[PDB]
Image (cartoon, rainbow, N blue to C red; front, side, top):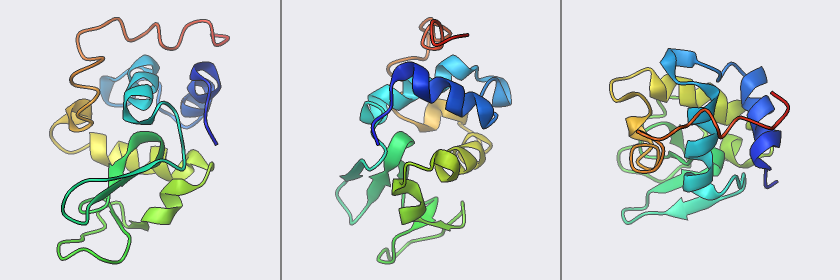
Length: 129
């Protein structure tokens, strides 16, 4: 599906995204919109048979496998299609392993370019919270 700022807020929040590694909820919703407007089925093909899927665009050469890449590690140790179902529990689950190594959310090129430095915790406000 396609989400609604608010609708996705409380979902991330039930999945432990509020504050995790000192990133408040707010941060999360914002990387969402500038990665794929809050579109789950959304995939995007980069240059070297590389692909970023769903809600947060977790890219295949590093985190998941879509059977095809000369590199392909599956650090998140899952199947990229886990990433294209409206069941967000494979994206959030993986995000936290992403966030956990070095670069924090600065690893979501659109979070460091569009919400880093802004008033993030607004993204979350009005969504009944």
